[PDB]
Amino acid sequence: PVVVDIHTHMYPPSYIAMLEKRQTIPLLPGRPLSTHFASLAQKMHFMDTNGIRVSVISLANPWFDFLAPDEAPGIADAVNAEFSDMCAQHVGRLFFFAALPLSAPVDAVKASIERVKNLKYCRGIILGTSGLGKGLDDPHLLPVFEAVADAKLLVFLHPHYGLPNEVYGPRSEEYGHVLPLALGFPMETTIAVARMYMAGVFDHVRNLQMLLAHSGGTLPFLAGRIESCIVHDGHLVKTGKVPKDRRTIWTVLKEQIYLDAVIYSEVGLQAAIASSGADRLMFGTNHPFFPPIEEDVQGPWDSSRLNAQAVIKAVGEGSSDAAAVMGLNAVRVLSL
Amino acid sequence: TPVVVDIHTHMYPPSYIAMLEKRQTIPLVRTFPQADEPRLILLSSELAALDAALADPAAKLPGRPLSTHFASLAQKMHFMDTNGIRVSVISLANPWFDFLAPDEAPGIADAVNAEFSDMCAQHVGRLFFFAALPLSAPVDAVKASIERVKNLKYCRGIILGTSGLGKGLDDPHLLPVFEAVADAKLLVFLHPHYGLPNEVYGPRSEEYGHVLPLALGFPMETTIAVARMYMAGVFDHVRNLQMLLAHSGGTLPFLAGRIESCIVHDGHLVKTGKVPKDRRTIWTVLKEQIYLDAVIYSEVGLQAAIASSGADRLMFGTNHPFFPPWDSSRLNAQAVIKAVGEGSSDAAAVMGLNAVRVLSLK
Ligand SMILES: [Zn+2]
Ligand SMILES: [Zn+2]
């Protein structure tokens, strides 16, 4: 009964080092930074306490997107080295998603892909929605998707930019970070994957595999609506973009898309399972972003247990589908 | 045998269309040489396609085709008879009266609402309507329109967008409007229109047609609006308020759990005492003050909507006549057969009986 967490983050000491040369951004305001973000000891302590055996860690947002094109490749190389080295400290319990210097020229990005492919304990790539600066449906980004897919690396798509702040209205500050995090993040994810599907990225790179943060954002709920809008669209019909042999979003959700379990609900989880299948769901925690305010921070976490109990509500404890989502799927797909 | 009710179905009265035919700014209706039917242009996402069509008469046709079905009450009844729909609760479609000048808004709103009442009178027992409010006008002019539609025959609720008076739905100046509507026992039908700022769809948005604004922008707009209402405490401040949400609440049934998790873990909210132990959760609101329409186009969506609000709070809709190829009305009826089952009490409830009870359709 191996338990694997595929949605878990760290800010390495080398990453925090360069964060304190900037007074622009990254930064009462914002989040408070603790040892849980930086200390690998605190990570393994969290894993032991919460019954987690193997973690596929990844750098948290904003990654390297804010960096200048000249410094970004060098910084990405150093941070990815740290990740590989951190994984070697606890062999068999730690793997990682590498981050790419997407603010650098395409050549440097493709060179990074070749390097991280040959880094120990690396099993994939984490990337945001901005791409090279014009989203994931940017034609210049196709050779990047092709290189990542050929390298046998899983793409972990993660939000950061959310939606433009105006949408939340002039009272947004009164609700804390609830609106950007609860809505902005999953909506950003959905738009990005929709733009990918509409541009035909999945068709052009059919070996590409995609893991989606927060159960696809809202994708499992909006998939049917997206399909209906596609088949009825006059512009797409006239231009011959909708033939009979066209791969529907449901087919892509079951052939090329994986979903995480960080949805905090059995309602949402049931929708995601019915979208991709119980074999294509993977348990996550989003550690260390949601710590208890009243309860002890060094003990068990509320965010991790809510996602765990939802699985038991969805597929039942003891069954093959439960052991798969909780870890055995990640072991299978990410070669652990 | 059980009565079928369509609660999501639209009309533009002829006078409303004529008003749009002479607009040079969105919303508008424009006739093109290469098309028989005029073009309906309602959205900010259509702005670029419009300007390109005016400069070059060879470019793709902007907006959507304006069929006769939008203004035809006869074609509405024909559609109902063909699909076995006994009752339609009709509503003015977006953008309603939002774009009207503050001075002329209440007068036009009063006239159009009276037309809708007269339309329903042509087919007694088969047509009811949601009214629209002159929300660009001062609050007292809005209030005056509420007590007017309160007295109108066959009026069963209010349809409104997400902009409110201009500051959204969490604007405290809008609270008395929610109160008045709730005190009048009128169901509020929240409906999308504004979507999301066009930049989120990227520089290739034109290549995808209407898919992204309609399939994503609309439901996301709805979700942000309701979340803003909820976070502001609108459901606590107006306890008798009942809300019908278009397209199964947008994304709300899927995101509800995430919203809840973010609230309890929000440091700023907990410290300011905005998260008490006796607070009404989003789950509670979804079962007490929120109804959802059954226009989701999937069994996955509908099942999630049923789990969130309950079968007694789901209501069948078609979005007639925004579906030109009649098949989406059959597709949305088909999902009910798989989710709860054909012939059951739950199906009969979703398909019409819930609407009969909640809207007092007699
Ligand atoms: Zn995360
Ligand atoms: Zn509609």
Image (spheres, coloured by chain):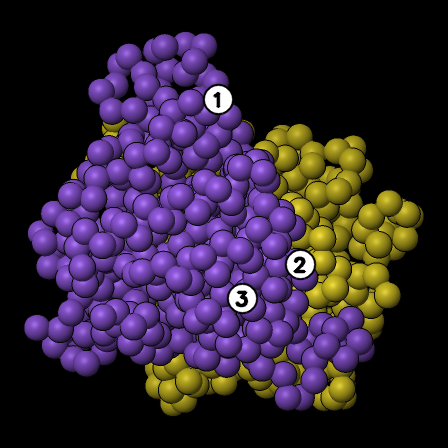
Chain colours: A yellow, B purple
Question: Real-space Cα distance between discs 1 and 3?
Answer: 35 Å
- Label whose residue precedes the other's in the sequence (1 or 3): 1
Mark in front: 1 vs 3 = 3
B326 lies left or right of B246: left
Q: Position of residue A191 (x, y in %)?
A: 49, 47
Q: Which residue is mark 2?
A: B173
Q: Secondary structure at mark 2?
A: helix
**C-beta proximity under 8 Å, tags 1 and 3:** no
Three-letter amino acid code of the residue under disc 1: Gln
Could you say which is closer to the camera, residue A25 or residue B261? B261
Three-letter amino acid code of the residue under disc 3: Ala
Question: Real-space Cα distance between discs 1 and 2?
Answer: 31 Å
Q: Chain of mark 1?
A: B
Q: Is mark 1 within 8 Å of ligand 2?
A: no
Q: Secondary structure at mark 1?
A: loop
Q: Which residue is mark 1?
A: B24
Q: Which mark is residue A56?
A: none
Q: Which residue is mark 3?
A: B180
Q: Label 2: few (<14), some or many (≥20) within 10 Å?
A: few
Residue for point 70% across, 58% down? A172
A206 lies left or right of B47: left
Q: Secondary structure at mark 3?
A: helix
